[PDB]
Image (cartoon, coloured by chain):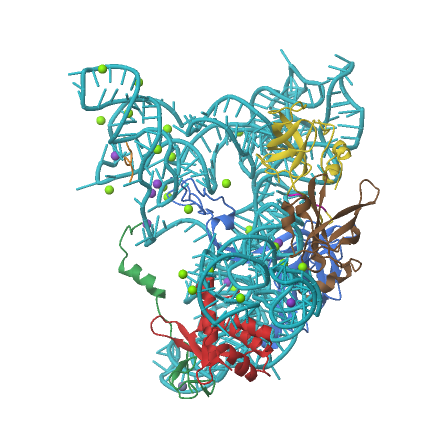
Chain colours: A brown, B yellow, C blue, D orange, E green, F red, G cyan
Amino acid sequence: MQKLIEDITKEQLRTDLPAFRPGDTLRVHVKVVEGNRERIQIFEGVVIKRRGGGISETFTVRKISYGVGVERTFPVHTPKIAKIEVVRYGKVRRAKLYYLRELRGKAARIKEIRR
Amino acid sequence: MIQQETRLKVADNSGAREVLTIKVLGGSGRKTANIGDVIVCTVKQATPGGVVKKGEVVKAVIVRTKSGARRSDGSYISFDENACVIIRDDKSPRGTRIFGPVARELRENNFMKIVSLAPEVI
Amino acid sequence: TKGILGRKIGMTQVFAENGDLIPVTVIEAAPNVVLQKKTAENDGYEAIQLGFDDKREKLSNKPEKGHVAKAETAPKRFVKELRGVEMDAYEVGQEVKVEIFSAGEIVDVTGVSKGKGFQGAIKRHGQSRGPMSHGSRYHRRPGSMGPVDPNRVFKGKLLPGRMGGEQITVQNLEIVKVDAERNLLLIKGNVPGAKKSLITVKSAVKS
Amino acid sequence: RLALGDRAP
Amino acid sequence: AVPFRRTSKMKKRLRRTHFKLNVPGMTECPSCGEMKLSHRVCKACGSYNGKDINV
Amino acid sequence: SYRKLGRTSAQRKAMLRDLTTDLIINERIETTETRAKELRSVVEKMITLGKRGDLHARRQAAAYIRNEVANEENNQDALQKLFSDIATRYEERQGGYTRIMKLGPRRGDGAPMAIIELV
RNA sequence: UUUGGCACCUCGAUGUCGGCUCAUCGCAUCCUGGGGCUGUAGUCGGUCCCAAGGGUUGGGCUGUUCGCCCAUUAAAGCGGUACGCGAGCUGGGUUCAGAACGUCGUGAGACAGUUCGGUCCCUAUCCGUCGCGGGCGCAGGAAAUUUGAGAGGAGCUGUCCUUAGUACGAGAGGACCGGGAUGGACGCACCGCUGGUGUACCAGUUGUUCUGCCAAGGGCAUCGCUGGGUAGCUAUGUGCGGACGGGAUAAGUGCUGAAAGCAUCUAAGCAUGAAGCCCCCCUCAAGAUGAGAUUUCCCAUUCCGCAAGGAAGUAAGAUCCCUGAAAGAUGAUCAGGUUGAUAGGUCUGAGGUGGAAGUGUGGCGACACAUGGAGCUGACAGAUACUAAUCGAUCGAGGACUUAAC
Ligand SMILES: [K+]
Ligand SMILES: [K+]
Ligand SMILES: [K+]
Ligand SMILES: [K+]
Ligand SMILES: [K+]
Ligand SMILES: [K+]
Ligand SMILES: [K+]
Ligand SMILES: [Mg+2]
Ligand SMILES: [Mg+2]
Ligand SMILES: [Mg+2]
Ligand SMILES: [Mg+2]
Ligand SMILES: [Mg+2]
Ligand SMILES: [Mg+2]
Ligand SMILES: [Mg+2]
Ligand SMILES: [Mg+2]
Ligand SMILES: [Mg+2]
Ligand SMILES: [Mg+2]
Ligand SMILES: [Mg+2]
Ligand SMILES: [Mg+2]
Ligand SMILES: [Mg+2]
Ligand SMILES: [Mg+2]
Ligand SMILES: [Mg+2]
Ligand SMILES: [Mg+2]
Ligand SMILES: [Mg+2]
Ligand SMILES: [Mg+2]
Ligand SMILES: [Mg+2]
Ligand SMILES: [Mg+2]
Ligand SMILES: [Mg+2]
Ligand SMILES: [Mg+2]
Ligand SMILES: [Mg+2]
Ligand SMILES: [Zn+2]
């Protein structure tokens, strides 16, 4: 990729994010604005993908909520995320965990790493 | 992305279990409906004893979809299923309980009773 | 009217202050130079001729070198006119820079659309296919050429042929950021043409 | 190749 | 679809206006002086760019 | 982009592997020009492995080079030649291990022929 | 546009219903725009006038056209174009040979009665349509930038909020005009985002076969299969558009005003007034032979000739040939051709894959862990003359006459 696009966008890259990879469990603290009030909704879930480069990098987290799978895809460097905290590092064998979309319950379990 | 013939789970206790989409509302040749859009639909499967009966034509608001929805901040939400809630003309749900998480987009369209009844709004 | 010539670098995105994610096109427009002023007396209409992008001497010719002598500049790769401008605001040799624009300003952007080569009626004119089964031998063909009675096809029966490579204007794009040091405009949305292609950025005509 | 032909019965 | 009328000698000859060969892109070989295709090894003597190739 | 050379993916791979080993053994082959042009990159990348010289490099090359005798006297394989003779020759040169010279059309099908050789 | 009447073209063949694909035209207007009258309070309507700019849905049933129905919609217009379009498609029906039912017939058989089944050929010559080159022209030869005669495109419209629960109305209900917001359908561009594809990217895996064996690999099995995926191309994805106005008008409304002491929109005179007309907006455009304009470059050579002309070598400049892609069927276009980053290679990255081999350790072993976000990596970025863009050659002005002003 152009150094020029890299240079224009460098200022908007967040530095405060922890290293995570697909299979890690995050709590993503999302700024939310229902009404005029501002509050933090937490989205806890498995990272199922992380694609793209630089300011365009996104990640997707998946949770089962009330018996329904939910995925939220965020720009890595969105200012709408207050913070990300890694709950547990998973042991997976690939970059994209789309096979989890078809699994529920015990079949959908990811082993932890001592990282 | 819900169109004519798309079947949806019903995310409420109105009596309908599954509906078939008869029509996306809101303009002449409109192909597709998304979260927060209203559809006309027929009840294909019903719970025995419910208020809403099999074969009834009803309005419903879509509250989750597999296609999901994009937000102005460049984030997305998707669900594992397509689901709707049977409504009256004033947007109030015909049932008394909503099951499963609904999308924040329903606040924007002024489906407040649904948003209040939902166990989670993501 | 105001305007400048640059190259399309590519696309990226920028977070707004409200946190909205704005896709942007990056146009790099090193200072354009006013090479000529056409006047109503001499030329019959008022315009300035902007040169952009210094060209190596080997790649120039004597007619070009002479034309850019008055502006006291190197030979330019791209030369375009702007009509509607304030004639008194410009002088031959004057540098026109990206900071003529400011963030929030509404612009029209003009460039040559990417080339697609020879394309059929489905891709080129957005026509329907015929059925793919049920015995069809009518898939990606262009439809009846017309009725019998004229003994001929009317002009504007659309058919296959070369697609793209056309001048295209997109109206009412917003300048998101101007970077004067790097000579960049960042424009909300997408604009015509391949990367490295010449883009003209003008103040919007419907403003 | 038609069953009957042009301007069939 | 078949020709509705035969083509006259004249129309046949007009059509063949552009049915021609061009002269080869040829240049004198600096080594041996025979003509060669520009940017190819000279077949006669096997030189290219003042070097023997077929050594 | 890259050329298809009128062949299926597998056929094209087979042919590029064949030509690559031919050029290692012979050090100069004659072929169609469009084949020569495709062969340059493929061959120069094998020489890069040879210059690396490590076992991982040799096995990457072994996945591509054909099992052919490059020298009957010494019983040297094409792979052994690549990793010894060719690699040593081009220790100091940084890329551009081949050159294409054009010959002109062959009788038979007018195909523009070329010599490709190691520099 | 119907059913017909007539039998004029076609029986050395004018394929025949419906649908599909592609439209285009008329206006007797379905919607939207403008109006007059109303048994027009308002909201709705009715009826007539102007108006063809754009728009005018998806399903169930039936071969169906039509029609009925469901659900929408601003609206679900009516007609023409060989019942538009079968050398464009379909072939359900109709319209051959088989078979059957009812029926008629002594019978063979018959029925715009029904039923199940039943070969849809053609390499485009010409015009025409859509693209793309070559030639010459345009009183010298060139390199750019242009004017716009003229042509094409676009032209649709909902809902909500507000004005205002105001006007109107017994109430029920409930506006105009004017602000603002946000959609549907349609179109243009583009890949940053979400996705799709991605057969010379990465990984897992079955069988068998080969590299002597182990280990590690290759071949074939749809790319063997399976999980991902870069560039590119893409829509369902993103951005943007039909804005704001001028000018002249239609129906309509008039003002002033006589013919005709009054009255009268009209005869003189003066206004107003539609989504329509001409512009405004987007694109093509001087072969616009009416061949336009501006800026800049070359420079008046040599030889034949009584000159008129002719030939030759050149200038500015361009091309052949070559490296290619942002271009592309091929030509063309564009970036380059050595004081050159044009392409490959190389080096460094990005992205993708997801943890190489080897070795070690642990385990009886399958395997696990470490070394180490490793190894590998088409097309993407930057750098670097290492390789190839060699050496050449070809083309290309010297500018007619007349008159007028200088
Ligand atoms: K006949
Ligand atoms: K046919
Ligand atoms: K015909
Ligand atoms: K003809
Ligand atoms: K994309
Ligand atoms: K001209
Ligand atoms: K290892
Ligand atoms: Mg990544
Ligand atoms: Mg279709
Ligand atoms: Mg087919
Ligand atoms: Mg005619
Ligand atoms: Mg294979
Ligand atoms: Mg008669
Ligand atoms: Mg005949
Ligand atoms: Mg009328
Ligand atoms: Mg008829
Ligand atoms: Mg017909
Ligand atoms: Mg026909
Ligand atoms: Mg049939
Ligand atoms: Mg009988
Ligand atoms: Mg009959
Ligand atoms: Mg009968
Ligand atoms: Mg015009
Ligand atoms: Mg990309
Ligand atoms: Mg993609
Ligand atoms: Mg083994
Ligand atoms: Mg075999
Ligand atoms: Mg076999
Ligand atoms: Mg001219
Ligand atoms: Mg290079
Ligand atoms: Zn020679």
Answer above or below: position of G190 versus B33. Answer: below
Side (left or right) of G124 relative to A109: left
Q: Nearer the viewer, residue C168 or B114?
A: B114
- Residue A55 lies, in percent from the top left, at 72, 58
Side (left or right) of G141 relative to C174: left
Q: Is residue E9 visible?
A: yes
Q: Seen from this angle, which residue lies furthest right?
A: A37
- Residue B72 lies, in percent from the top left, at 72, 47
Answer above or below: position of B121 versus G292. Answer: above
Answer above or below: position of G105 versus G327. Answer: above
Q: Residue at x 83, y 41 (%)?
A: A36
* Residue C145 forms part of the magenta stretch: no
- Residue span colored magenta: B67-71
Could you tell me how many numbered marks the image carries?
A: 0
Q: Nearer the viewer, residue A62 or F71?
A: F71
- Residue B51 lies, in percent from the top left, at 68, 23
> Residue C152 is drawn in which quadrant?
top left
Q: Residue at x 72, y 32 (%)?
A: B98
* Residue B69 forms part of the magenta stretch: yes
Q: Is residue C31 visible?
A: no
- Residue B57 lies, in percent from the top left, at 62, 26
Q: Residue at x 54, y 82 (%)?
A: F84
Q: Main secondary structure of the magenta part?
A: loop
Q: Nearer the viewer, residue G378 or G42?
A: G378
Answer above or below: position of C189 versus G177. Answer: below
